[PDB]
């Protein structure tokens, strides 16, 4: 059981807006953005449950591009070596952020043949800090089992 | 003196359309797209002259993404090792194409902090073939001394 702060902003694929995970408690059957680890591309994926795991100690993780999230010590992030717990990460280690690049011709027509292959931006960690006890939440994403929260790829429930 | 076929399509920065270089003969004071070799970014740049060098033997060069141009044997293209003549290139050698990537957030806001640094796509050569004698043209780009023709970075006159 791992989880994230209720303030964490979930990117919602149907609306193009974000909502904090706490505000989605008890909602379901909505789409988030997930990485497909086989293709390294982002796909929309359905949330089947959003739940609170109680009050837990959370830690703020920050990356070089300023992405930040508060998560439990056992919460997993995606490194080049696979999924790793927050309390196993070290500074300068890269974690996966989503990236959305579009490739156009000089005439502003689509030019997908020049698109970089992966939808991941690998960003180094610059801070990991114990922050305090908060109500924490997670969600279930059957199939791909990950989602974007605060513009970071995080693992869903197991 | 090197040159390209009159059919070669010049990307015009003000209009977002292309025109064959022959149709620009005698025109000037218009902007094309050029690579800045110091920053590796594309910039608009002014054409001061468009001229015909006569009838010359031209060669078709083609890359893996299907970019193709007809140019003289001494016409230069940009490799990772600098500018090289058509008659010095070999198959699988990469040459520079422009690329225009845009980086957006998952909410479709600009997200330039994740943009790849270079505006070049390095594409391998798949064919170099003597084609025939044609009227050929080039142009002068003071300062950056290159331009995009048939979606390939080519050197301007000297």
Image (cartoon, coloured by chain):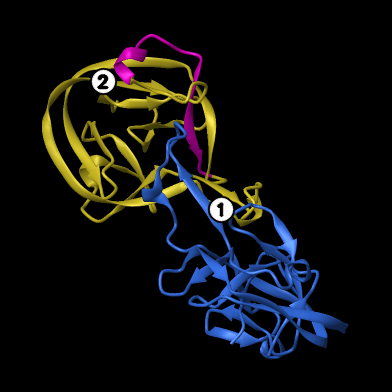
Chain colours: A yellow, B blue
Determine which quarter of the picture holds residue B92: bottom right
Image quarter (top left, top right, bottom left or bottom right) of the N terminus of chain B: bottom right
Residue visible at 45% across and 24% down in the picture = A12
Q: Position of residue B89 (x, y in %)?
A: 67, 86
Q: How far separated are the C-alphas under marks 2 and 1?
A: 33 Å
Along the viewing direction, whichever of A17 and A54 lies nearer the viewer: A17
- Reply above or below: B52 against B113: below
> What is the residue that sits farthest to the right in this orientation?
B132
Q: Is residue B85 left or right of residue B43?
A: right
Is residue A37 shown above or below B155?
above
Q: Residue at x 19, y 36 (%)?
A: A60
**Dot 1 falls on which chain?**
A
- Work out whether residue B8 or residue A10 is closer to the camera in this orientation and state it: B8
Q: Nearer the viewer, residue A59 or A123?
A: A123
Residue B157 sits above or below residue B35 on the image: below
Disc 1: CA contacts within 10 A as few (<14), some (14-19) or many (>=20): few
Residue A33 located within the stretch drawn in magenta: yes
Please determine if labels 2 and 1 lie on a single subunit. Answer: yes
Start-end of magenta stretch: A21-37
Query: Is residue B21 in view from this perspective?
Result: yes
Q: Which residue bears the numbered disc 2?
A: A6
Callout 2: SS: loop
Task: Read off the chain for label 2.
Answer: A
Q: Position of residue B8 (x, y in %)?
A: 76, 69
Q: Helix, strand, or loop for circle 1?
A: loop
Which badge, 2 or 1, is on the more N-terminal residue?
Answer: 2
Q: Residue at x 38, y 46 (%)?
A: A96
Residue A74 colored in magenta in the image:
no
Task: Say the numbered circle drawn on residue A117.
Answer: 1
């Amino acid at each position: 059981s791992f989880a994230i702060s209720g303030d964490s902003l979930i990117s919602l694929a149907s609306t193009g807006k974000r909502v904090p995970i706490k505000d989605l408690l008890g909602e379901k059957d909505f789409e988030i953005w997930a990485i497909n680890e086989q293709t390294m591309k982002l796909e929309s994926a359905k949330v089947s449950r959003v739940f609170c795991t109680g009050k837990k100690l959370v830690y703020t993780l920050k990356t070089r591009l300023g992405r930040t999230i508060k998560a439990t010590a056992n919460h997993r992030f995606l490194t080049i070596d696979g999924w790793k717990r927050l309390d196993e990460l070290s500074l300068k280690e890269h974690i996966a952020l989503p990236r959305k690049l579009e490739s156009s011709s000089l005439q502003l027509a689509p030019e997908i043949e020049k698109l970089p292959q992966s939808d991941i931006y690998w960003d180094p960690i610059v801070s990991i800090t114990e922050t305090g006890v908060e109500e924490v939440f997670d969600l279930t994403v059957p199939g791909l089992r990950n989602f974007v929260a605060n513009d970071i790829i995080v693992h869903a429930s197991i």
